[PDB]
Image 1 (cartoon, rainbow, N blue to C red):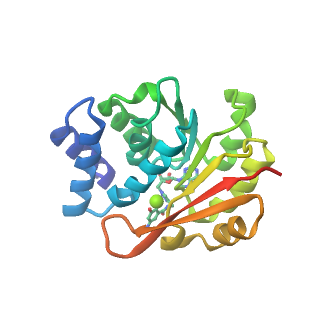
Image 2 (image 1 turned 30 degrees about the vertical axis):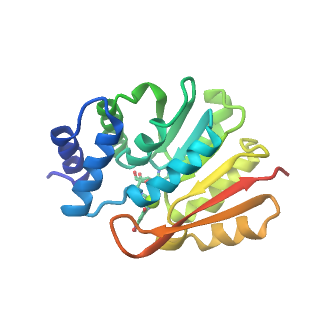
Length: 214
Ligand SMILES: Nc1ncnc2c1ncn2[C@@H]1O[C@H](Cn2cc(CNC(=O)c3cc([N+](=O)[O-])cc(O)c3O)nn2)[C@@H](O)[C@H]1O
Ligand SMILES: [Mg+2]
């Protein structure tokens, strides 16, 4: 009784300043550097994420896997007014942590949390949420869903030329099938950003894959 995710949030509520997203991010990072490792994107990879976001200024972002709401907070705090983030989370407990994390950050009005698995929700985006195409996609869910969900996004017509895919953990725990596909495919221009597994000295990285169209 009493999960790590609940402890992380409790620490944020005690040490972070309400309505200040930088503060919420620093609290989580501190908690996870000092007390318990947890699978947030972390500040090192979060900084690359920030740079990618500022470059494209997406109006509509889709995130796969929210977890505690760390990357959701990172991204939604950089979004222009009227720009939105959709985040898919299959575990209702983590989704609740995320909602409260975003509420504390004062970012709740920029984000919609979708409850359910990506494979079930993605085919419903156009019909049930009036989504034309996506400006950007952050992949941070089950590693072996990266490729299937990409092909699924393409099938559902959610990708246009210019859609940026940003994938966490392509080295650790690794997504070798996703990497071979986007790199080998002329439908994706790919950039690797070398970095470190969150809160550790193990080499990890993000992959940016830009859809070129059919
Ligand atoms: N199909 C899915 N649809 C929606 N949400 C999903 C799905 N699969 C997992 N999630 C969510 O990802 C979050 C966190 N997560 C991520 C994974 C797969 N990713 C990792 O395991 C991971 C693992 C490490 N690691 O092992 O060092 C480091 C990282 O940065 C990671 O993202 N499992 N739970 C959880 O909230 C879970 O509900
Ligand atoms: Mg990750």
